[PDB]
Amino acid sequence: KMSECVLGQSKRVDFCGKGYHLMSFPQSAPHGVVFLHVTYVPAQEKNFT
Amino acid sequence: KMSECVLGQSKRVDFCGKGYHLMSFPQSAPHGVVFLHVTYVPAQEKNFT
Ligand SMILES: *[C@@H]1O[C@H](CO)[C@@H](O[C@@H]2O[C@H](CO)[C@@H](O)[C@H](O)[C@H]2NC(C)=O)[C@H](O)[C@H]1NC(C)=O
Ligand SMILES: *[C@@H]1O[C@H](CO)[C@@H](O[C@@H]2O[C@H](CO)[C@@H](O)[C@H](O)[C@H]2NC(C)=O)[C@H](O)[C@H]1NC(C)=O
């Protein structure tokens, strides 16, 4: 995830958060790592022919 | 990796070597496999407005 979510933009569904992946920022934790996933989510659909 | 690095071109970051993946060639090793990763690396940048 560090390489594919933070050092690039992924197309893998659900791999880098929910929505269309834009970017990620790492944060450190005591024995691990926390990823902040930024995604694009569409809203307010309308009907068309 | 045999499927995704050798039988195709991957966009996965750092999965098929360092740089932009072009192609890979397998070699047999005793009890293992060796991947020769061919990558594209840019060089000699200039700055512009
Ligand atoms: C697009 O049109 C359809 C109907 O063709 C709308 O469907 C409605 O759906 C609600 C539930 O969400 C039902 O209670 C209504 O009875 C439906 N209407 C009809 C006329 O069947 C749908 O809501 C429309 N989509 C948008 C985004 O407005
Ligand atoms: C593009 O311009 C930037 C400055 O805007 C260059 O960075 C400077 O590089 C010199 C030489 O290494 C350093 O002494 C300066 O401290 C740098 N400035 C800053 C603000 O970091 C950069 O090297 C230029 N790129 C190229 C290819 O020439």
Image: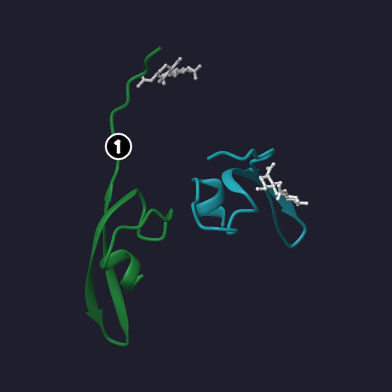
Chain colours: A cyan, B green
Quarter of the image holding residue B3?
bottom left
Some atom of ligand 2 lies within 8 Å of the CB belonging to the residue at label 1: no
- Does residue B44 appear to the left or right of A46 in the view shown? left
Residue at image point 28% right, 28% down = B44
In which quadrant will I find the N terminus of chain A? Answer: bottom right
Q: Position of residue A49 (x, y in %)?
A: 53, 40
Residue for point 64% across, 53% down: A17
Name the chain under label 1.
B
- Judging depth in this view, the residue of A27 and A37 nearest the camera is A37
Q: How many marks?
A: 1
Q: Which residue is mark 1?
A: B42
Instruction: List the single residue furthest toward the bottom.
Output: B31
- Residue A8: x and y in percent read 49, 46
* Residue visible at 36% across and 52% down in the picture: B18
Above/below status of B2 relative to A46? below
Counting from the top left corner in percent of width and height, residue B37 is at 28, 60
Element class at badge 1: loop
Mark 1 crowd level (few <14, some 14–19, many ≥20, 10 Å Cα): few
Taking B27 as reference, is A26 above or below it? above
Q: Is residue B18 above or below residue B46?
A: below
Query: Residue B22: horizontal and vertical position, in percent?
Result: 26, 53
Q: Is B30 positioned to the left or the right of A15 in the image?
A: left
Badge 1 amino acid: Pro
Seen from the viewer's position, the closer of residues B29 and B5 is B5
Q: Residue at x 49, y 52 (%)?
A: A11
